[PDB]
Image (cartoon, rainbow, N blue to C red):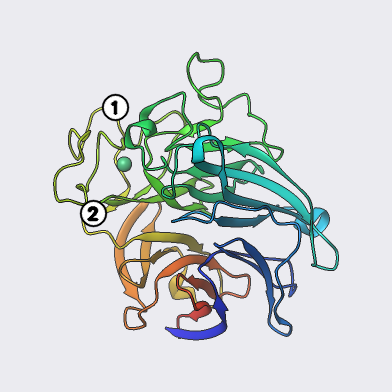
Amino acid sequence: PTVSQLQDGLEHPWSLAFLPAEQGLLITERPGRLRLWQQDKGLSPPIAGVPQVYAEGQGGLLEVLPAPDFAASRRVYLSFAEPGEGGKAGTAVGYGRLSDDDARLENFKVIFRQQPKLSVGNHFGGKLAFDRQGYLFIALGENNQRPTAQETDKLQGKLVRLTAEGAVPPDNPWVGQAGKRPEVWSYGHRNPQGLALNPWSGAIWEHEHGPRGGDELNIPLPGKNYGWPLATYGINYSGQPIPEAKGERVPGTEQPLHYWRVSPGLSGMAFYDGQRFPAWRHSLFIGALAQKALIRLTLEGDKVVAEERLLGDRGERIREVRSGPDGYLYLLTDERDGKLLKVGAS
Ligand SMILES: [Ca+2]
């Protein structure tokens, strides 16, 4: 593949999002800054009005996602780790309006908070995605408290579906059910760092880290249990089993679409529906942090039929993957001197 380094000097960049036409790209730096990159103008100073964050461990400023109607509204959603009571943090999601001159995020306000707050630095999740109807999906980790992913009254280890304003859609699976959070779409997730709308089927797909082994790709269905920590393809970091695990397959829990017994460290995900590189059409691209590579899965409908590895000689932790309107892939690398990369098939 071809690789062009478009920008360096990004401190642990986490998310990118394209703005319309040639207006550029927004990029988050996990320590807590939002930037705008454009091909002629380079990288902006930090944009004003961004929330303060819990910038410890894996937390900080996470996803940036312009609203589907950004051209009209200039609305920009952000996810981030937010401090709370008792010195524990949790994920939060809000939005503001990017000013006409790109200098300031105006009137930022939180619309959703993970509760309770249980993290001391790990497993925020944080990816965001809109579906075809404009509903907002939010992927949440279990804050490193493994059993809470199974608990229906806790927002740990859940995929959440909200309206554009953060309200609960009345057809969410748990609405009206005692002891269950009505924001929840699916449960039993560990630490999801991939979330994307399949452009052909209209289904949200998700991926998540396993512990020592067992990273997973899922197609999450409403009200379904993805099994963490009762079911897993991984073990604990010590080499002992995860204490709560009953098996790789556990009845009443849904299997992953695809799994990796040796964890690449999945991060970022994009379906390729461009015209520039026809050989890449109907592929799903996923970053690998630990294995420092880009994964390409060939799809036949909902089936994964082949797995390819790219960029394995570059030595960069791939944190973010987006399919650009110009037909190239755009990546961020997770390092102190983090990079924005433009990647093509040849
Ligand atoms: Ca699972």
C-alpha distance separating marks 2 and 1: 22 Å
Q: Which residue is mark 1?
A: 252
Which quadrant is home to the N terminus?
bottom left
Determine crowd level at label 1: few under 14, some 14-19, many 20+ residues with C-alpha closer than 10 A. Answer: few
> Which residue is farthest right?
100
Q: Is residue 85 above or below residue 298?
A: above
Mark 1 belongs to which amino acid? Answer: Gly
Residue at 67%, 45% (x, y): give it: 94
Q: Which residue is mark 2?
A: 213
Q: x, y (%) of residue 276? A: 55, 77
Classify mark 2: helix, strand or loop: loop
In depth, the one of 97 and 299 nearer the eye is 97
Q: x, y (%) of residue 54? A: 55, 51
Determine crowd level at label 2: few under 14, some 14-19, many 20+ residues with C-alpha closer than 10 A. Answer: many
Q: Is residue 82 above or below residue 282?
A: above
In depth, the one of 182 and 322 nearer the eye is 182
Quadrant of res 165: top right
Residue at 55%, 35% (x, y): give it: 85
Classify mark 1: helix, strand or loop: loop
Which quadrant is home to the C terminus?
bottom left
Question: Is mark 2 in CB contact (under 8 Å) with mark 1?
Answer: no
Ligand 1: quadrant of the figure: top left
Using the image, tell me which numbered label, if any, was put on residue 269: none
Residue depth check, mark 2 versus mark 1: number of the one nearer the observer: 2
Q: Is residue 133 above or below residue 273?
A: above
> Is 127 left, or right, of 112 in this rendering?
left
Mark 2 belongs to which amino acid? Answer: Gly
Q: x, y (%) of residue 175? A: 56, 20
